[PDB]
Length: 488
Ligand SMILES: Nc1ncnc2c1ncn2[C@@H]1O[C@H](COP(=O)(O)OP(=O)(O)O)[C@@H](O)[C@H]1O
Image 1 (cartoon, rainbow, N blue to C red):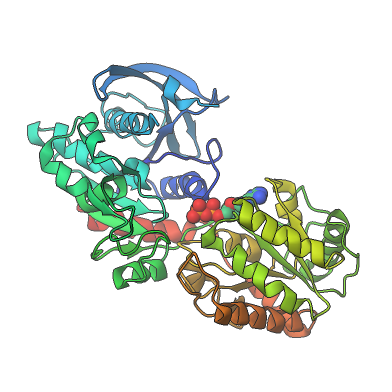
Image 2 (image 1 turned 90 degrees about the horizontal axis):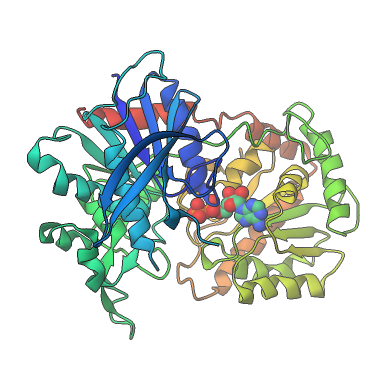
């Protein structure tokens, strides 16, 4: 009931963030700390971070051949030991395994060779009685490395490791010839062994970090009970890949959100701050502000749909694009924000091209506009092919922007038909294709939603969306309940 928890991962918010691998490592740790636990977060140091004080300690780490020395910078925040692995690989305007071999290894060092009494309730060295939580493929090998170099000769021993699957789309798939460069022994080789892209003319033996991660760990996890069930089942399509393997007894906990960064009542990018009680009328102002900014006609009576995502197959921009002509039979505005492929970037761009005054396709990392979008949009459209957690709909609801979404993944957990949004049905999972039945559902659902807008029930829906707790408080209790199971 009083465990030491060490979180490892490539990205770590606020410092190194892009996808919701960042947010997870930024928010879950302190929430877990606030539950009276010794909680640490090891991740690489990508830049010369300000509150990042070198604690001088250095390990030397065996990578391929070269013996590599790492610096350990520290910053101790929010009840949480934030540790940063320093090294010149971690600064690059290939040698990809190297860096994260570094990472997993260094992360095995910081628990012992660091004395850190900053915590008012816990002193000394973290110990060798740990629970490791490994995140995404980048940390796969850690479980392995621990059994290789520690458990045989008395170090850690009764410790355990949980592997968290943030997105099955990225597995860390490498040449099988590159194996030995991990200074792990053959026993573990079999766990990495992968037959990639079978039957297709590109099939090839491969090394798979996630696979290793998954197979070697004491407990496996993902970011959503429905996603867990989608995997355990068969739907395990990471798009290009499929099933990877008969996944076994995996466990899913819905993510929380960074409720401080996204807080309509304190947000500083948007024209009008609000809570649930003034949402409707402030959202109108934000909406018009948005309408201007997007050079669309300013009119609060026009329902505005929003799409915000990386323009990749997983987030269904092609599908969104196909549905536009249909929706343009209605008096509605659609604002899309994201950046990804070319084919999609121009798919949307052509849509703006065809209906100006009604469609605006924006292509950039405009964080300010995302906020503005969240504040002013009436519905968020999230036609995902697959969706492990989803941060966009959590953000949306926080801002009272109900969601019309694909009935896949974490959206099934977080978006309730009638209370906080509108399910669309599940989309064809053949990423490379655009099912006309899908184009139909998407269109259809969006039409319903926009018809709801600006009616009493809609305002209730908004209120529901705002009145949830989407902090890490509830999540963190679920996580710990799992980290309990692990005996340590
Ligand atoms: N153009 C953009 N500008 C600002 N933020 C963006 C943009 N595109 C995506 N995002 C943010 O990144 C996320 C998109 O999906 P993401 O969570 O990265 O999926 P995954 O974690 O599976 O990679 C959203 O949560 C959104 O807030």
